[PDB]
Length: 293
Image (cartoon, rainbow, N blue to C red; front, side):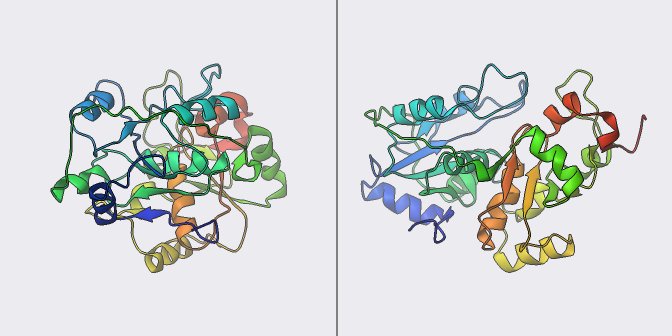
């Protein structure tokens, strides 16, 4: 009930009952943070049609540093507080996040992380996502949600974040383990990076790949701790050592941190800039591909 571990994962059942008990309000806020590649699924319309009762739509496109040239970068403290405060969330709120991904979870772990990096320890992800909420027949609705605004105080927690400069030195110090959550193809350089002009695939030198999807079961639920643990281990990632997670734009890297958290390591840091920023900033000698160089 504190970062002694907070409850990172919440069940559909737990959620439906809080819902039924009138638990949603200032003390319990629900957010849909679905995002899809342009032209595929329509995250916001989907939300307007069907949403867990009382939930608000969390738009990452809005909540980020619009001025950066890179993708999905954290907004500033103020920007964040402002945003969250308007969704009626305060420092005392237990925040539940979910997404509509078919996989069971995609963007939700990113929002979980953002709350943490800004100092809020009381937030969880709906294990199984909307996919399961539906499958189970829990109540869905199209009525609008209009929480009263709250005041939220945000404080950046630097240790859960890594910048371009910090990752570049790590190249020399090797103090932290670097784990890439993208699909192997993109990690290897065999497949291309999507939705980007002149963006090559490949990975930072010394990185280890742990494709995000490997942490979820066929049904879309998080695997269990014992399984998570065995996975990091088969990967040669030691949970007792520092670790930085990176991916394309600092989104699915969040899955490595949730899983490490569930295994008892809450200090996984996220390289927000990620591959997108890296490719455009570092010397080409710092990365590798299974092609063109």
